[PDB]
């Protein structure tokens, strides 16, 4: 319907986790959140998964949550099923929150990702499309997008921004 456009925070959305269960994202109320689109066959798959796991291990106890959305729109680098994707992330000891595969660009993009890219701090410079695998959005404890990091920005580079939003 498009009726997601009236939302003004992360907490108005729901999305299915990687086991297929619908997660109401208002569960993240009051937490600091990173949302990222992931892929298993990307040149930066390893550095992003290793460093997202490191961020989660070190900062979950400070209220950080990480929401990972698989996406096959970037070089068909997430071709596997949700069950295969779940198995893949086990080699990295992923313990943050894993979601079912989605599109992030175009008319079929999941409404959460359409919304993320329309935010004042989520929309980028000359257009808001997701450029490639492992874009990250940093979301504050009120559910607002505060920063967007591109595919080349390694997760450890979010660390310098993260604690101030605690």
Image: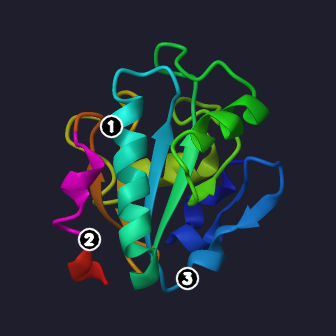
- Give neighbour class at mark 2: few <14, some 14-19, many 20+ (Cα, 10 Å): some
**Magenta highlight range:** 153-161
Residue pictured at 46% horizontal, 55% vertical: 35
Alpha carbons under labels 3 and 2: distance apart: 16 Å
| Residue pointed to by mark 1 | 47
| Residue pointed to by mark 2 | 162
Give the mark nearest the N terminus, 2 or 1. Answer: 1
Alpha carbons under labels 1 and 3: distance apart: 28 Å
Look at the image and tell me in which quarter the C terminus lies: bottom left
Quadrant of res 49 = top left
Q: Nearer the viewer, residue 34 or 103?
A: 34
Q: Which mark is residue 72?
A: none
Q: Are marks 1 and 3 in contact (CB under 8 Å)?
A: no
Name the element at disc 3: loop
Rendered position, 43 above or below 69: above
Q: Is residue 127 left or right of residue 117?
A: left
């Amino acid at each position: 319907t498009g009726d997601w456009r009236s939302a003004t925070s992360l907490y108005e959305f729901s999305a299915p986790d990687i086991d297929g269960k619908m997660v109401n994202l208002d569960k993240y109320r009051g937490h600091t959140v990173i949302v990222t689109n992931v892929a298993s066959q990307c040149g930066k798959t390893e550095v992003n998964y290793k460093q997202l796991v490191d961020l989660h291990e070190r900062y979950a106890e400070k209220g950080l949550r990480i929401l990972a959305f698989p996406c096959n729109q970037f070089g068909k680098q997430e071709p596997g099923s949700n069950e295969e994707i779940k198995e893949f992330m086990a080699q990295y000891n992923v313990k943050f929150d894993m979601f079912s595969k989605i599109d992030v660009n175009g008319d079929n993009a999941h409404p959460l990702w359409k919304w993320l890219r329309e935010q004042p701090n989520g929309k980028g410079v000359g257009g808001n499309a997701i450029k490639w695998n492992f874009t990250k959005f940093l979301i504050d404890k009120e559910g607002k997008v505060v920063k967007r990091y591109g595919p080349m920005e390694e997760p450890l580079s979010i660390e310098k921004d993260l604690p101030k939003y605690f």
